[PDB]
Length: 231
Ligand SMILES: O=C(O)CCS(=O)(=O)O
Image (tube, rainbow, N blue to C red; front, side, top):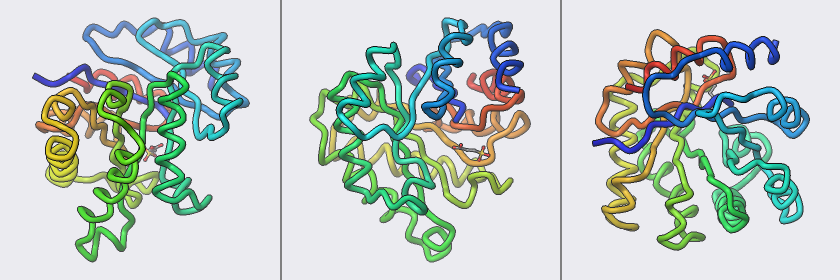
């Protein structure tokens, strides 16, 4: 059976109110990730015990230490625009992941191919090269602290979701590599989340696929339906 699912979100006061009042009637880890400036309020306000707060993109020893001290134990790293806009390479992302794990963080590590990479049939090579870089900086025990988020760059914010077949093919390819390079025990416990134009309507169908363990989506009222779709 699948490991514990995750639903992560990547008028905020009304939004925190809505989440706080939501009964979630199954086992799922919910995560709200936000920029430094909003962390303090999110932690002050978000009290639902099935939710944790996550930082994003911290890459400095002292910054990570400060976050942990403040009670932040999760972090999202390597998200799409980090790579295609800011210029974080596969190795920079991998180093940030290694540092975070070393500082005691649960890490949602993001990987995914661009439109051209997809169209030219290079999804597998790109995505696997990205995760291999991450794996290079980790030891086996570290994977207990890692969560993989697969997001086709062409599906992020474009309104174009991957089909269930596309998502499943990508997740299975990732899990098979983890199984063979890291170990089948690690593969079986690893959460691989899908992200990119997930909504209330399409999430539950995606979750039905063998290798989908949850979602990364925007912080919006419909995230509640995304949480419900994780079963
Ligand atoms: O933040 C992401 O990872 C996904 C945002 S969206 O594609 O659902 O609009």
